[PDB]
Length: 355
Ligand SMILES: *[B@]([O])([C][N]S(=O)(=O)C1=[C][C]=C(C2=NN=N[N]2)[C]=[C]1)OP([O])([O])=O
Image (tube, rainbow, N blue to C red; front, side, top):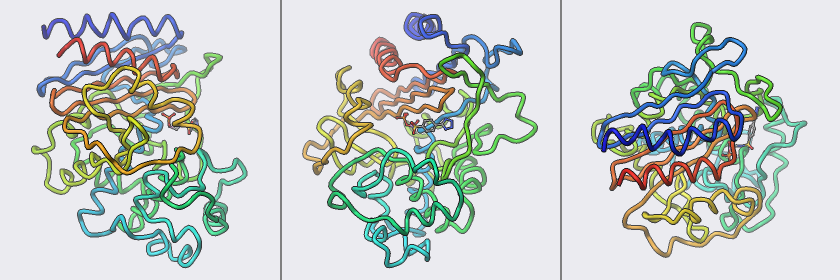
């Protein structure tokens, strides 16, 4: 039955490469503290270079899981409180309307007036500040979820301030080493550049992620399959990790509110396990991801939880899912974006099939 993991991944993930003309894929499963790595295709088409365990992929919004973790770590070191407001850490925002939004609300997208992206004209340090100064409320604060790069991006920048280090150094010098990660970066160094995949766009042109305002906390991490698998292992089995990072991790698992069947935890999305396929699919529906939705308090506290997160940049897809009580998880990394539904559906069949 260990011998079936490979066959399951070939049945469910492998056809997506022909169907979506994807150059390269890495799929990892972890089960009962045993890791399985499946690699497909090429990290770079023009160089005929294979996907392998050194291959670095862009994680996109799976990056928000690291930001959430950095938030949990800073809360439990007493550097921040989730009841604080950003003006306490970014002086220049004190007494402004955005300083009525607390850090949890920023992290969990409920400021009530923040869209998916910054405006394209917002780019520099000063334009970012200016944007947050000029910010004014729209929906009642804390009542409306709209998925948002600037919201969690500011939470990220506040966490770095509370730690007196820029955000990239928070991850690379504190958070990634505490998790045992060897090849995860906000900035891929010179000596690893030959391991960094090209991404491929919808016209199969090789591309990489562009700079943008507060990109690191929102979508700027790159990692390998083994690293991601270690991250899922941390999440599934955090007793082995330093106390500090354990408390951080636990903090990311606590659901804060519900949108019907989807609970919003810190970074992660949480569901009752077992979740139906449609529950997992509808979590990244146009309605949930693209438009405001009024949240409610958690009514049904799930006893057995599962967690997932999707991520995309223009050239890369990512999906990450784990279920504590089954001691199982999966990671998919592609260097071409494929529909979220496909990633979700393939992971559902594999994880169900293994028990
Ligand atoms: B995350 O992956 C955020 N998705 S996004 O639509 O906001 C997005 C951010 C950044 C890029 C990009 N910048 N430079 N190159 N590519 C593209 C898209 O959430 P998710 O999983 O997509 O819902």
